[PDB]
Image (cartoon, coloured by chain):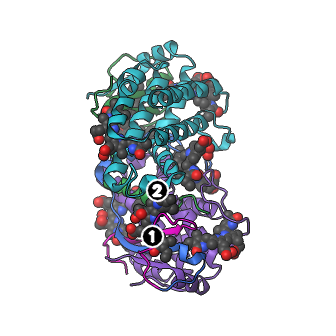
Chain colours: A cyan, B purple, C green, D blue
Amino acid sequence: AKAAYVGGADLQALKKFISEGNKRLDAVNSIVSNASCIVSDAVSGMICENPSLISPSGNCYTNRRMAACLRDGEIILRYVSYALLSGDSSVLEDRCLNGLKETYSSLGVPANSNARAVSIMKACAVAFVNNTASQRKLSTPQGDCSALASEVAGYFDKVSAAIG
Amino acid sequence: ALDAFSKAKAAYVGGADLQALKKFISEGNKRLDAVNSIVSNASCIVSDAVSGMICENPSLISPSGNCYTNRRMAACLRDGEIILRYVSYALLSGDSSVLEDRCLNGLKETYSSLGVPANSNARAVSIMKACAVAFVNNTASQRKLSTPQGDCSALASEVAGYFDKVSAAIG
Amino acid sequence: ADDKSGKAPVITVFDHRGCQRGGPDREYKGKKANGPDDEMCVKVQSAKIAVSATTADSVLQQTISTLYRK
Amino acid sequence: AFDKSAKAPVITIFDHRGCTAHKNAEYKGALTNSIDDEMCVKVQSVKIAVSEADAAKKLQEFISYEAKGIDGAYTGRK
Ligand SMILES: *[C@@H](C)C1=C(C)C(=O)N/C1=C\c1[nH]c(/C=C2\N=C(C[C@H]3NC(=O)C(C=C)=C3C)C(C)=C2/C=C/C(=O)O)c(CCC(=O)O)c1C
Ligand SMILES: *[C@@H](C)C1=C(C)C(=O)N/C1=C\c1[nH]c(/C=C2\N=C(C[C@H]3NC(=O)C(C=C)=C3C)C(C)=C2/C=C/C(=O)O)c(CCC(=O)O)c1C
Ligand SMILES: *[C@@H](C)[C@H]1/C(=C/C2=NC(=C\c3[nH]c(C[C@H]4NC(=O)C(C=C)=C4C)c(C)c3/C=C/C(=O)O)/C(CCC(=O)O)=C2C)NC(=O)[C@@H]1C
Ligand SMILES: *[C@@H](C)[C@H]1/C(=C/C2=NC(=C\c3[nH]c(C[C@H]4NC(=O)C(C=C)=C4C)c(C)c3/C=C/C(=O)O)/C(CCC(=O)O)=C2C)NC(=O)[C@@H]1C
Ligand SMILES: *[C@H](C)C1=C(C)[C@@H](Cc2[nH]c(/C=C3N=C(/C=C4\NC(=O)[C@H](C)[C@H]4[C@@H](*)C)C(C)=C\3CCC(=O)O)c(/C=C/C(=O)O)c2C)NC1=O
Ligand SMILES: *[C@H](C)C1=C(C)[C@@H](Cc2[nH]c(/C=C3N=C(/C=C4\NC(=O)[C@H](C)[C@H]4[C@@H](*)C)C(C)=C\3CCC(=O)O)c(/C=C/C(=O)O)c2C)NC1=O
Ligand SMILES: *[C@H](C)[C@H]1/C(=C/C2=NC(=C\c3[nH]c(C[C@H]4NC(=O)C(C=C)=C4C)c(C)c3CCC(=O)O)/C(CCC(=O)O)=C2C)NC(=O)[C@@H]1C
Ligand SMILES: *[C@H](C)[C@H]1/C(=C/C2=NC(=C\c3[nH]c(C[C@H]4NC(=O)C(C=C)=C4C)c(C)c3CCC(=O)O)/C(CCC(=O)O)=C2C)NC(=O)[C@@H]1C
């Protein structure tokens, strides 16, 4: 539960190990600094396209179910952000995805709806990484982050495949 | 204009009552779309305004800043939401009577005695204003509500004026 | 396999170049880079993810008003 | 003068044209035989509240000082 901190010389070394270190940390930053919005928008969009999810028979009906769903969206988003920080999907697959479809099948968490929630979070993340807004609307130097965008997109695709 | 919900319990206006309500406020259909575009984005508006206030003045969450500690940040996030919602009701009713009477009157005196910084509150309100105007004209990055194409600049100017009343009251 | 604990890695990114924090930077326990990396830091912590009833109610209230329609 | 109760009007706009899946029992007044029967404005006075735990989550997002979405000029500093 204790937090790890990577600054100074350790951070210098880290950015020598992962590719495009500086841009990669900006990419992570742009996602985690907007985490609650990404998760809520994806769950809200999942539902607005399928209102039966919040009908009395839907899997997001009641505050208890909605909170568990928003929680799961954040868990998944955060494991994806750690995959981007790390540069591979090993922890994402082992600590989050492996066994998750089986979990959702036993709970009856709808796969068609999770598929859409994941694809929206993916759309959010790609837009923040490959942000084509003007320089004046960016907190980072304008440049080409398309490779990082494609990488994070791949991590979401691994989520989709695992629980599809 | 009409303060129609001044009366615990929720009020529901549909069917015949709604048909009448839209005649009592100007541009009834457009107005309800405008209100909806704001309220449906309320969490992002408040978060963006409080975050923007902070990123322009990082010391607000330093140990000497007014948003320091979870208790204070919670009170500030709450107040941002309270103010946005009273503004949204001014836009629903078409005037500022409730906004002034039930939110703004006495509010500056309260913030003065608490030491809530007015220059920082001004920026939060200013950002919320910029958000609301863009949502009314559907020029925000997110455009999740569909409307017939038309000119809502009058409504955008109206809601901007309500935010200006907030700024003048607590400035 | 997932442990069903509800935990996930919470990452905080501190690009605080130019910052005068007013207090010491004591969280990072390693050695200095003798460069701008000494003003930046990454925090990673495995934490239980928790969502309040207020948040869940807020998402519902802002979703029910945008449901697809005819 | 406001009463310090932290209560505020929560508006919920239900433009639910075509939504027969939900029976419109909340509004009890007369109908019109028109789309106005398929839409509804809800207003309720609610005590606005933010928990300390939820405020801690927002602080974790904000403390990068780069917590901004797509919109808006970057006006922040460090
Ligand atoms: C169509 C959008 C839809 C599908 C498809 C589906 O599966 N569920 C759908 C809608 C839905 N409605 C509610 C609850 C409320 N709906 C209204 C507006 C409705 N009620 C009226 O009296 C009139 C006009 C005369 C209309 C247009 C209201 C006021 C609701 C409740 C408010 C409250 O304070 O509780 C839901 C939530 C679950 C439910 O069916 O009760 C859904 C998912
Ligand atoms: C500059 C942006 C700034 C001004 C101006 C101001 O008034 N406060 C400012 C920054 C600030 N930092 C924190 C807390 C943390 N800062 C860091 C990074 C720092 N710590 C290190 O060990 C290193 C070494 C390379 C660096 C660059 C971290 C990790 C912080 C806390 C992590 C945690 O688990 O909480 C704050 C919060 C209040 C405080 O000063 O403690 C501010 C406001
Ligand atoms: C895509 C990700 C976006 C983008 C990013 C971008 N960043 C660039 C340079 C840069 N970023 C940082 C901060 C970074 N480094 C850290 O250690 C941490 C926090 C721990 C973060 C956050 C730094 C320090 C730098 C540059 C340092 C230097 O001396 O040059 C660049 C420029 C290219 C590059 O340096 O690799 C880009 C580009 N730009 C975009 O347009 C998108 C939105
Ligand atoms: C500015 C706000 C944007 C704009 C709005 C716009 N809406 C229009 C017509 C319209 N809107 C509604 C929904 C509204 N009515 C309700 O009762 C409720 C919910 C209770 C809502 C929400 C309706 C039903 C209609 C049309 C009704 C009809 O019978 O014609 C129009 C067209 C002009 C007008 O009708 O006044 C506009 C314009 N359009 C934009 O482009 C901006 C972004
Ligand atoms: C119901 C009518 C419904 C919605 C709810 C909404 C859901 C939705 N959102 C997207 C795409 C993006 N959402 C983003 C979120 C943010 N942008 C910001 O500035 C703040 C910080 C964040 C919270 C609002 C982003 C960055 C997105 C990428 C750009 C884009 O708009 O595409 C989508 C897209 C799905 C897809 O591309 O397949 C949906 C469905 N939309 C609704 O209809
Ligand atoms: C700290 C790094 C910081 C910020 C946070 C941000 C503060 C800020 N925001 C604006 C303008 C708008 N913000 C909007 C919010 C949303 N748009 C969406 O699509 C989602 C759903 C909403 C929540 C994120 C909107 C609609 C804005 C209007 C359009 C625009 O691009 O401006 C501003 C602008 C002030 C001005 O115009 O003078 C600021 C300062 N900026 C930061 O640096
Ligand atoms: C939102 C996009 C979904 C949806 C999600 C729900 N999940 C529910 C219970 C649940 N979720 C998990 C997996 C979660 N826990 C972990 O430890 C990890 C990874 C490390 C993850 C991704 C578990 C183990 C459980 C059961 C125990 C618990 O609640 O913590 C849930 C409530 C289930 C119920 O009440 O029967 C929901 C609603 N629901 C949707 O409709 C969309 C697709
Ligand atoms: C956020 C943009 C601000 C900021 C806000 C803070 N307000 C604090 C306490 C507080 N706020 C109010 C007004 C509020 N209550 C109402 O009933 C109404 C209208 C109906 C509103 C607008 C009151 C009455 C109070 C005191 C009682 C209470 O907390 O509920 C506060 C904590 C003050 C302290 O304990 O020292 C904060 C931080 N702070 C900022 O830095 C930005 C500019």
Of B136 and C38, which appears nearest the observer?
Answer: B136
Give the chain letter at badge 2: B
Residue type for callout 1: Lys
Q: Secondary structure at mark 2?
A: helix
Q: Say which residue appears at 44% left-offset and 45% top-offset.
A: A36
Image: magenta residue range? D1-29
Label 1's element? loop
List the residue tagged with mark 2: B43
Q: Is the residue indicated by label 2 positioned so its CB lies within 8 Å of ligand 6?
A: yes
Q: Is mark 1 within 8 Å of ligand 1?
A: yes
Residue placed at 39% from the left, 30% from the top? A101
Give percent across and percent down for residue B109.
Answer: 37, 73
Q: Quadrant of ligand 7?
A: top left
B130 with respect to D58 (left or right): right
Note whether A12 is above or below B117 in the view shown. Answer: above
Give how far across and how far down residue D21 sits, in percent: 48, 63
Q: How many marks?
A: 2
Quadrant location, the N terminus of chain B: bottom right
- Asked if marks 1 and 2 fall on the same chain, the answer is no
On the image, the x and y values in percent for residue A100 come to: 37, 30
Q: How many other residues sit within 10 Å of disc 1, few (<14), some (14-19) or many (≥20)?
A: few
Residue type at mark 2?
A: Ser
A157 w.r.t. B24: above or below = above
Q: Please report, as a chain letter, where disc 1 is located.
A: D
Residue D4 rendering spot, x and y as whole percentages: 32, 73
Please, is residue C15 above or below residue B93 in the view?
above
Q: To which residue does mark 1 refer?
A: D23
